[PDB]
Image 1 (tube, helix red, strand yellow):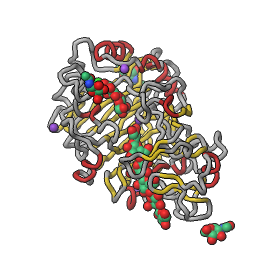
Image 2: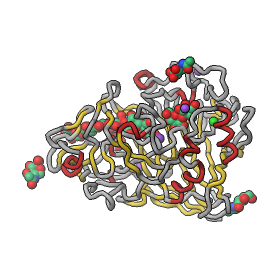
Image 3: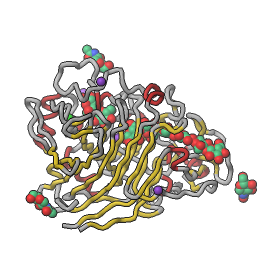
Image 4: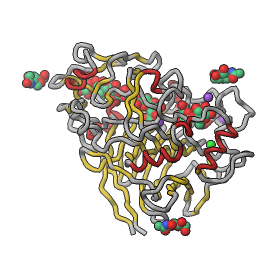
Length: 430
Ligand SMILES: OC[C@H]1O[C@@H](O[C@H]2[C@H](O)[C@@H](O)[C@H](O[C@H]3[C@H](O)[C@@H](O)[C@H](O[C@H]4[C@H](O)[C@@H](O)[C@H](O[C@H]5[C@H](O)[C@@H](O)[C@H](O[C@H]6[C@H](O)[C@@H](O)[C@H](O)O[C@@H]6CO)O[C@@H]5CO)O[C@@H]4CO)O[C@@H]3CO)O[C@@H]2CO)[C@H](O)[C@@H](O)[C@@H]1O
Ligand SMILES: OC[C@H]1O[C@@H](O[C@H]2[C@H](O)[C@@H](O)[C@H](O)O[C@@H]2CO)[C@H](O)[C@@H](O)[C@@H]1O
Ligand SMILES: *[C@@H]1O[C@H](CO)[C@@H](O)[C@H](O)[C@H]1NC(C)=O
Ligand SMILES: *[C@@H]1O[C@H](CO)[C@@H](O)[C@H](O)[C@H]1NC(C)=O
Ligand SMILES: [Cl-]
Ligand SMILES: [K+]
Ligand SMILES: [K+]
Ligand SMILES: [K+]
Ligand code: NA
């Protein structure tokens, strides 16, 4: 994708902190993912993409399309409901016909910030108070290229500056641009989302979902892949949520997840609970390595919370067969043994391959979305919906009829998530 000229691209400002075993406030900024943008011909206002289909006059091939179509600048607040205030980022849900957003932290105007998380602690504050059933305010990391692909893929000029280069563990085929090619060939409009479709290519890479949550439930989920960085997959071999068989590909779509409610701890997180989601709170996450160095492999993910200045531990599992309050080799083996299903976490290298994702360096993503595929039931309801009574089926209190996108967009359009005070450093430094 090319760089358009009609609207200047100005990344809203967002500060964040680096901490030492003493913190330094870094100047940062955020960009909007390329899928939300206007895509038009080079030096013309003609759309390359309108509604849920491509303009075959310009985009007669995957390559020509990327050479000949440009992404343009965004009105962050006015069109997408994205604002920043100091160290705080607010993502609105419905803004006209726009639904949510996906944003990336920048190191400069043309590069995503890269985080090296092994043997570090990462902290943020969140307000989920305005996130009802069926929404997901996510803060997580993916193994994207810092420059968004510009150095590797010649047709890609727009790069990180225009939010190009997304990949994740679901191998998304809904992306308009992947690896310097447009996703034109085989494009199939979704029958239910007027803006969206699925192309023949998907963009796979490692994903560390440190935070997927709403006011009801939260989960922490590493997802490894066969290779850490971008791998371009084709059609149904992609696996993930955009394919016939989620387990057909090279990334783990399920992950090794820790949701306190799923693990039997139903009084921990939610309205007026131990972590009271009517108010903001701080989430601290540690990435422990086998040898205690930045170059060891990932042994354990640890977690705690702070609210009203009070430290609140991650609660331990109440499910017979699954112990503790950390994610480690024993926990991941125990989860799949007890809850059952496809061993996709092991098959894609588990924590060793998660570490490879992390060692490559990862981009920070903040998003707010609803889910046409599963209505977010996997996060905050009983799932599968016919598995009531079985261990791990219940993930939160939402009804199994909840989370229908057009429903929640009509009823709860004013929903929003605010992320703030991002901090990273050595353990005990944030
Ligand atoms: O025509 C001339 C005039 O153009 C004006 O500019 C227009 C332009 O013409 C128009 O084409 C453009 O339309 C864009 C809309 O403004 C924008 O809202 C819309 O955004 C969609 C996007 O198309 C779609 O791909 C995206 O899909 C989401 C999906 O909903 C979501 O569920 C999924 O969630 C994932 C999470 O992000 C992730 O964290 C998690 O891990 O996984 C989730 C999935 O499991 O993410 C996908 C995307 O990957 O949804 C958004 C939001 O609804 O995009 C339209 C383009 O396709 O608008 C322009 C501005 O109006 C000029 O302004 C004017 O001057 C010209 O004259
Ligand atoms: O694809 C939807 C959602 O799936 C999540 O994994 C589920 C899996 O779908 C379900 O069959 C199993 O019982 O539970 C896992 C974990 O909740 C996955 O973790 C998400 O990233 C994904 O969005
Ligand atoms: C730049 O675009 C405008 C709008 O299409 C057009 O008037 C002008 O001729 C363009 N430049 C060219 C063709 O070099
Ligand atoms: C249970 O529901 C899932 C999801 O629709 C489906 O795959 C399965 O066939 C259903 N029936 C039974 C008995 O599991
Ligand atoms: Cl869980
Ligand atoms: K601002
Ligand atoms: K994802
Ligand atoms: K309910
Ligand atoms: Na299975």
